View: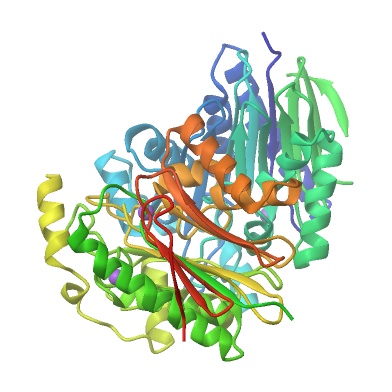
Length: 293
Length: 296
Ligand code: NA
Ligand code: NA
Ligand code: NA
Ligand code: NA
């Protein structure tokens, strides 16, 4: 049976402060530890990517759940998706509010409806049927995010391969700062924000949402592998095309069916981390290979 | 410069009794002929697919705009998207209510905003801001679909086009499926799934079970194949082939390559479709019941 792997990513975004890397690092390391621990007891791929995306949602440092950017009204609106590479089962929520873990809600859509995607008010309806807690907007808005906005006036993801050779992906975000109300970016859109398939691999993406959607980056990446490119070569084709075709920047993380993995990005910085073989590989900048504490 | 062409379709579901067949064939002819009228008259492939689908939305016999299927909670929530192959420029909307024409809001999303996709409350407010009229919910509603939602206690409309300047586009629009959960979103607004447009390959607009079409990203898979060497019909067959086996989904698509070539195919029992090219109307519902007239 396969040796399991988890890869995580924060945003494929701008350059970070020298002091705050410390802080961002430990965010990647932590969510990846939650993912690799899960695989380390025969959790499934969906378990790992969800608990890993769960970690970063909870973390007010990352642009997802608590920590989400604000829309044009000072308000957090959230998208996410999760996908099962064996049978292509999937779940996604878009433009949801007053909840803590949009990724946990995306799994609930997937596991307990015959639908794959719920939006806005029907998505709240679904959450409360599932007895998901309402929290105050305040509890998701950093003092920080209000400043990022008023000047103008991040994504998190995970891929894993488990003990049985299943792949999966999770991606969650608060979107782009100042976005129109009800703007949906790539995150809850299969093939854009992520894709996962046992006959190929899994991908979660980050960066400019409209650009990712337009070139179908996640599924695109995996086409290149399907043609026998390396996971390195594949991700260099998709992001390079995204740049030359739509002037969009981003980054991505991928695991192929046989367990090869990479983080590549064309933006300034894509914070990432990976666990495989009791060893952890951490970076923010264009990499520590280190024991699993 | 190329010979312009539009292809239009309706839902990809089951058997259709002869009495409904006629108005459906009727409406598909208005759609093909409206879109073509724009292409003949110098217009863009984006303009032209916007054309074919507004006719399909305003026409009651098709699950998009007027005559959209009802969600579990007796309301209309509509999905639409539109793409320009020129630059891959796109606009989209999900869970829109109480407007006549979702595809127009979608194009307004491609042109008037920095985004490609708005939904529900957000999409309603942009529609206020662009001067989209706020039309009472019940006029979208129809007895056929009232009967149907009652009995439950499915349709999509689309077009692709090639223009006389070489450019390609698709538009897709839907009400979803019968007794869907509130705020359910299917394939029809998701680029790569409910449709894909790329001047360097061609354009495709899908029909059928939204959830499957999303799982396999049906429209972009037909294109990958057309890139690889496959003819439009082989690519149709194979992508359509894979949704059936891998995820046990049925549906359809229309496609039109950057070379002039077009096809319409389905794995559902039926799919109302018409193409217009070189001064003729093509149409059909069930496999090779092909009839061609001359289009004035
Ligand atoms: Na967070
Ligand atoms: Na990002
Ligand atoms: Na209609
Ligand atoms: Na349909």
